[PDB]
Image 1 (spheres, rainbow over the protein chains, first blue to last red):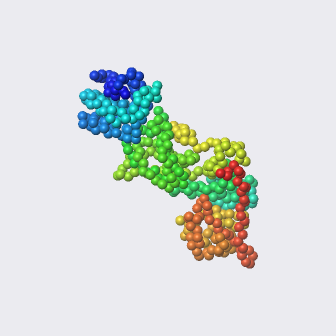
Image 2: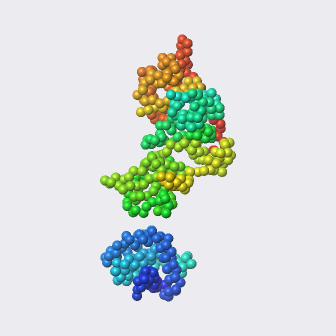
Length: 141
Length: 85
Length: 149
Length: 105
């Protein structure tokens, strides 16, 4: 029942802010505070994987659509749980920061579009049948 | 060259002197040795380990499991702890 | 920081885990922090082809009693880089246990741990049954041997 | 191909090894060097049948699979007694006690 566009907009804005790059159905402020804390906690627990994806990425204007569609597919291939959604969000921040490192900043708008479309199409079904975002913040808080 | 290990029930076991030195306690006693507390069924197994150890140590051959019957384990354990092998 | 650990080299190395022992072999990999991690076991007499990386550390124990096993006639195994498309062989062979330790193995398997004291044995041997072969204990011993080197 | 043996007579047991190609007379000479008894004054048996000096250890039934170090094969020994020879007599080993109840699954 929450706008999935604001959730991904406010998240990539925070991931690009931690690197100092800046950027451009109600939504409560609590779902944003939990998603940032969970993504940072996820990154700390799997720092060996965070540096792994940041190196093996190799982002180009054409493989960017190839990398996103292949990684997100392999990420949810077993199923959909809240821990994999946090990894899904964190993977979006990885491909956005790595895009602006190689000075491909316009890809942030394309990645934010791909994340919003995948949430509304392939993940909106599971999130509703699990209490929504208000249940996700209760598992972490 | 051989030695004679004698069990508590009078059985005499003749093994090669090289194999008997696997037990450091047997080496200090050296000829013949009398074990007043190791019966024949236990001392015969100890001699079988001597021939087993000498053949398979420092060998790339596939090493088989050394069998030990359940009814002989406690006695063979005490016999091995004294012999240091 | 730890002494015995695997180097994150990320260089693939093909290994063959050949179980040349009557025991069910448990492969043990030492991660990049020296912690031992368990891997799928091997039935007696079987062999499996393994994806590993160069510069990693492997142990092999009995899956039921953690008894020490020799891999290529030693305790540790380090996969080197392959050549001519041949996998590096890791022959897991049974060691020549001392007659005492082999006796300790049979008694531990037959007598339950809470019944080691009800055995009419010496009090010293009672403490030898309770000292099960432990992987963390062998790591501390195999680390001090590298320091003496 | 090496076989591992247990030459036994009365309360004596000899632990030795030999090749399957080695003859029985050669095994008797091994007993000779140990017990100081000539091979002609010896009668070697397998189970219950008397072995001839011409046959090899393999031809009698001693193979590396049935004569391992951890479980050697038993050979009977008989010493010449006055004008005739010896009736085979191998005194058995001791009997271990009964299994304590802290061992039966």
